[PDB]
Amino acid sequence: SPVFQFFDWVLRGTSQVMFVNNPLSGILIILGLFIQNPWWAISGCLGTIMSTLTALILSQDKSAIAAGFHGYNGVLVGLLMAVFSDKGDYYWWLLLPVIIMSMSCPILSSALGTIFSKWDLPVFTLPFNITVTLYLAATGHYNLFFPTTLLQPASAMPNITWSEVQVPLLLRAIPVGIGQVYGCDNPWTGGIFLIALFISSPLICLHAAIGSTMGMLAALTIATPFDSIYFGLCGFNSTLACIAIGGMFYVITWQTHLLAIACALFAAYLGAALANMLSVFGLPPCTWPFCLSALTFLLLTTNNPAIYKLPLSKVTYPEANRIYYLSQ
Amino acid sequence: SPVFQFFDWVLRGTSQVMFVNNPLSGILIILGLFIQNPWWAISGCLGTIMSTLTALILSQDKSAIAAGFHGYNGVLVGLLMAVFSDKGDYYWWLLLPVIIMSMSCPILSSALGTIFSKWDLPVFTLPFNITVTLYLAATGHYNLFFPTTLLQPASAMPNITWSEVQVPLLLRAIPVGIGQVYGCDNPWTGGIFLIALFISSPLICLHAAIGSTMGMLAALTIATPFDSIYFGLCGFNSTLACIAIGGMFYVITWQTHLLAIACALFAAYLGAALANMLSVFGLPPCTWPFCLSALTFLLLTTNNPAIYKLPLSKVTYPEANRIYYLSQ
Amino acid sequence: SPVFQFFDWVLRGTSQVMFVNNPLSGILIILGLFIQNPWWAISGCLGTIMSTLTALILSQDKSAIAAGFHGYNGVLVGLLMAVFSDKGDYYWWLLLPVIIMSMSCPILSSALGTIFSKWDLPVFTLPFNITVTLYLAATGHYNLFFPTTLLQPASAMPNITWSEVQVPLLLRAIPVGIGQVYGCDNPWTGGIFLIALFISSPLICLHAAIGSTMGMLAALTIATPFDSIYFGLCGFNSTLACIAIGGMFYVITWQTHLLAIACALFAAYLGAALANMLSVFGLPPCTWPFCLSALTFLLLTTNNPAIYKLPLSKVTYPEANRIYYLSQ
């Protein structure tokens, strides 16, 4: 039936943000981001629905819509306009942009995939980055209709007291850093997202955990204030980068594992850089470090046979990737 | 004769900003932008002349110079350095940059057309965007020689009173929005530009009008202050985008018409975004939304046979485009 | 022996910033940038060593490592994090970023060279630009560990008194402008760099000198404060651009010489633009004008047989380039 098929597609899109396609994973992600905030859940689901509908009415590929490729850029757009909204919870007018902006996610996801299909790169999260970045710039904090939260560049040195670092909270920055991948800051939401990852592929779960760890460690190395680390804002780019490079696209080996750790570190440092830069505009580093770091590590060409990049046409969860590559 | 041929080329370049090649259209555009301000007219004509001369002395293609492709990026550069000049009218020293910057328009119009000819995209207005953006950044408002007008990021919520919206002025935002492509804010100038468009191809005129309408409507939807709408600053990117997508490059159908309306809306929202972003640097959104939106809609690939993208080698006014496509 | 071969590679990398491969040139550059500041010398040498080691352990091409292609992006990264460091000389902890950031130079130098090898363009200094730009954004002036110098956008008109211009200092802006490629402001360092260039190829030395001259002249034309000109900050992009376009990649003719002068002027104006832009973020224009201008002049396509672009696989010092081209 068309309705159940479409809802399967939107569930797969919800799960696809973290490289997993299973529908049960989508249900778990949706449940977690309902646990965090039901308003963000409604906005993100509306974004996914409208993005998939646009991909349908734009005659996009049906084998890519059915895999959630055209819906994972809508859930994030909805969620992150429900996050950066100063108007508070249940500002229903905000759903009107959530539709319109989501409708532009497929177009970008097509256009950039005509610039990137020549080098066989995925359009990781760039539709979301472009769309929500232009939304938050167009509206801004000083807007009558859809004001956004005020992000302001640092104007003084942080007062970091290293004797008060909460190591339990520092460890909990891992689940929340994975939770923050959807913009959710609730450790239960991060744990449910991690269960959703583990159900599909354990390698993705492990790489997300170590990506959060690398992000928090990088934030510690560059003297990031502890509140941002505890909140999980320093990890989600690293989690996604570690998932993407380590196993999903590169076949999983120890050399690819080290490359994924390096990509997580590069994505964390670039996340700090882009947070400090875009804070001048009042913008967040919404998955930009991920796109830049994952693309600069996928474009990497090495004479090492162990670092092998799979064709996008034959990419699946890392275990199936390695089985396919060993079968050749 | 070389002189009359060169003046025909500069007239075609003046007209080509709005996708029209006729020389009579160029004369009408020049007359309109003399009606607005003769100083801007002199600067823009100097820019066109110097850009075409540079394209001649750089051994550029003579079938593209003769079509005004190397002159439409000089008229805008001259006009928009005569617009963003705090020194006032008839500051003759300003002509010295107007030459130099214009001389860099062909080079970009070649260089970018080596990066874009692989995907068969036109270098829409990027020479102008890069050149005048680096000019206004290099000089800035605080410069002894060629100071520019002060564009400053918003620091408080607008005091918009919706009972005082002047619907006649809101409608007049369409002709002035069309005339603002060249920087002119005079409704008579916009009307003359619209006559110039209509003489060549009625579809371009209709798409420019509905592009201005979409720009003003988008500005209303995102609570843009009414002065900017009345001035026509919220439409010109939308007008150009609607001209480009709807008929000029995509063959004209109802699906392409809807896509052109969507591109106008996307260009308006991206224009607000880029105005809010570049205002930090003190820069205007000088045709950047057009380039980004038109390129992201031309790169769009759909399985719909009605949305057909013509090769650039066989692109002309939309009526001839459709006749050629139906003849196949 | 591996040790002497590796040190030869790092010397060639040190020299390769200015397009010269000789090891004696590398020794002279290192001596000059020890004369300027030994701390910057230590940081830059550490950057070169770590970048070459990373290129070795990433299975990069050994015919490119042996030519210093993977080391010239590390010397600059080390030098320019030792320059933009508010902590003062001999802050040994700064060596820890100098390693990590340098290790990311090869990856970019590979990734961008997969995007640019399709148009046969070199990755000029983009690894350095991206890496140090994200370092200086991530840390910034307000950082507890590795604070950077405060670059702040202009907030008032300069008080330039044209009767006090020191023409001897204005001329000395040429050697110091050449020496500022590596960050050194000492005229003796610039002279030693110029000797190092002249030993390898006189055309590179001449083009560097006239590039500094074009940079200082452009700075004079756009009313740049005299302190920046004397310091040599307005020339190094122009010197490098004149070296690259005039002889190194384009075969050396009078038309290519004029094109190199034009590229130096464009790089100087773009350097002012990018200094004014990136100063909002607190960032310097660290070789960005060079990459943008050299790439937009290499992508230039002309019907002039004298303006000929050599394949990167057969590029050497300009004299050998012309001999090869005449031999055909």
Image: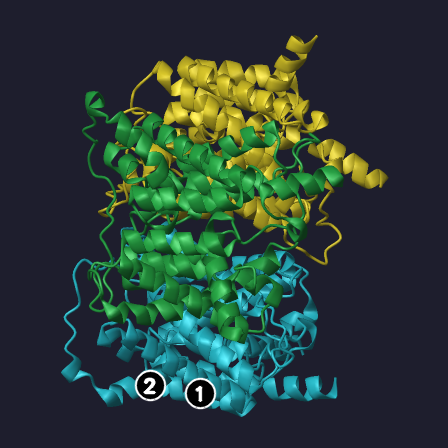
Chain colours: A yellow, B green, C cyan
Q: On screen, A205 above or below B328? A: above
Q: Nearer the viewer, residue C322 or B113?
A: B113
Q: Quadrant of the N terminus of chain A?
A: top right
The dot on residue C194 is 1
For label 2, the crowd category at 10 Å Cα-Cα, with few meaning under 14, some 14 to 19 and many 20 or more, is: many
Residue depicted at 25% across the width and 90% down the height: C168
Looking at marks 2 and 1 on the same chain, the residue that comes earlier in the sequence is marked by 2
Q: Quadrant of the C terminus of chain A?
A: top right
- Residue B282 percent across, percent down from the top left: 28, 52
Kindly indicate whether the residues beneath marks 2 and 1 are on one polypeptide chain. yes
Residue A235 shows in the view = no
Question: What is the chain identity of the residue bearing mark 2?
Answer: C
- Residue C287 percent across, percent down from the top left: 43, 67
How many labels, in total?
2
Q: Is residue C224 left or right of residue B59?
A: left
Q: Secondary structure at mark 2?
A: helix
Q: Secondary structure at mark 1?
A: helix
Q: Amino acid at mark 1?
A: Leu
Q: Nearer the viewer, residue A2 or A202?
A: A2
Residue depicted at 48% across the width and 35% down the height: B206
Q: Amino acid at mark 2?
A: Pro
- Residue A237 percent across, percent down from the top left: 49, 38
Q: Quadrant of residue B138?
A: bottom left
Residue depicted at 55% across the width and 28% down the height: B258
Q: Nearer the viewer, residue B234 or C115?
A: B234
Residue depicted at 45% across the width and 81% down the height: C30
User: What residue did someone put label 2 on?
Assistant: C187
Q: On screen, A169 above or below A249? A: above
Question: What is the chain identity of the residue bearing mark 1?
Answer: C
Q: On screen, B187 above or below A176? A: below
